[PDB]
Length: 181
Ligand SMILES: CCOC(=O)CC[C@H](C[C@@H]1CCNC1=O)NC(=O)[C@@H](CC(=O)[C@@H](NC(=O)c1cc(C)on1)C(C)C)Cc1ccc(F)cc1
Image (cartoon, rainbow, N blue to C red; front, side, top):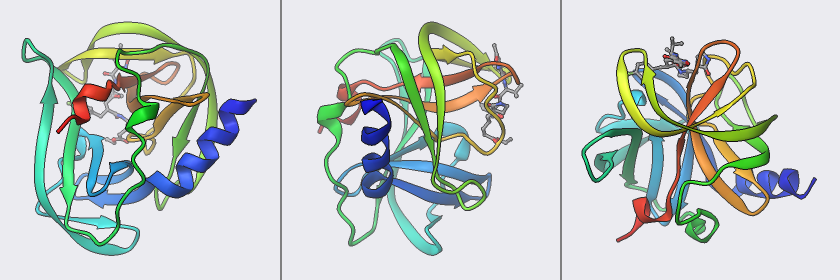
């Protein structure tokens, strides 16, 4: 329902195709020159965005208050573009959902939407040997190439896709405070 239309608007204004040396990812533009990627994309000093090479001014790998990996990297892009500020749609606390849509946009998987259904609290995740906190899980067979995908519910941006085991998928939860100045 209304979830899907919200997801479509977010795609056009805030979701971009990127490529690093690690491959193709979806990127969420958060506000102005600030964006977020899965940590394992390992963005360097230059990144491909929508067929242009773009300088990266700064990058920070996010951890929680105890130091646990959140599997998210915040980057500031050297770009003319200024993302519409979508932080008001990110909840203050990690939020589950009943009818979520995953928004993917890479060169190999352009502009696609996947109804993943319920997104439930999971927490600690061992992701190919890398400990990760604050994850959520969906019972949907997500696949390689979908990392960075944005998990949304009606009027809420709740996660970034980071992994899966063939039958289930997992996202890093989003909190508004990650993006505070
Ligand atoms: C290399 C290409 O990379 C990509 O395409 C990025 C996106 C894919 C999407 C997966 C691809 C598959 N189904 C999915 O949804 N993500 C991964 O592959 C990650 C690994 C897993 O998902 C692992 N899963 C878990 O550990 C796992 C644990 C439980 C529990 O559930 N899944 C692998 C075993 C698949 C990549 C990763 C490697 C090292 C790290 F430090 C941290 C992350």
